Length: 354
Length: 92
Image (cartoon, each protein chain N blue to C red):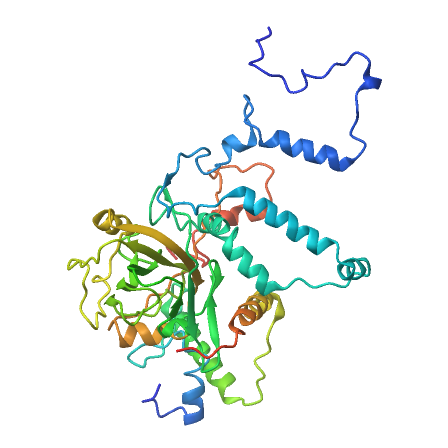
């Protein structure tokens, strides 16, 4: 009994008559490439991608962006062609390249990455650590504006916060400084959220440091709502992630519901959903910059919980489910002696009536 | 720990350093025992751990030997976050 193949059968297209006149894969590498090309297409039969959780596969993106920067392409193409002409025709670069001596100027690369491609890498790096799922819940914002967050670890020492980097609570015991560039017509709102580590409510976060109504680059001049609170992870649970967000606002907005007491040590006072917050201010607020850092328990934390929050410090561990044993049988057949010890309740003799 | 006289001051202060994980906000050093179901042996285990912490602290010649097997990734990640911290500009 044969069924009818549904649509394309993988090799159907090639003509087996006269095999000598078909080109071949002479290279193992070519084969490799064509193979992966095939592995990426959506076949009509049960496949690896299907059962292994492709993260929903196709998703129709809710894009809340800052609109794509307007550029004429012919200008770019020409200027680039010319830059290439100038760069290649130089005998210095040829002599240097042949002898394996050259260096690429990392700072300028950082500048170009920032200017063009970087804002796209940001998107998928945020996607990686899931800065989207927990905050905007369906929605992707492309990080248009460059965001530099930094903690001062000494008089001369600056700790950078890059998206995805690991930082210690010690350096986060102090307030950060921020760099981004805007003229003054500007109106900004900046946010620092702890995306996991909420003890009572798994779907809720902790606003650490919230700032509102900022002209240009002036951070001191923006009205602050939540004064700065150093990250307070738990000893057990590893590697929380912290998100720095930027929003443009059109008219200066003031919101009393969001306002918090000045010292504000209590934890239930800080309970947050980026979702609801952005629902409240949605029309006037457009998401802009993104920078996040990953942090795990460190010595300074004990000082926090006791001194600030007047609370005992929680310690968590890792529990792996007890190894599965089949039902014990009255006469285990053909089993080692130690079989008896798999169903052992506890290790201690028990003399029952004795 | 601060109130216990039966331990000398150097012992007091160094048992408060290595063990700071089991110290309590009331200044309490907390020991836990489980295995036996006869509380006698549990007491013996706690008193033994206590004698071992006091012994290891009281012996000044202990070099606290570091294993590179569990801490290699820690040293690598530490160096790597050190290369980012290494940026030198006066801030604040």
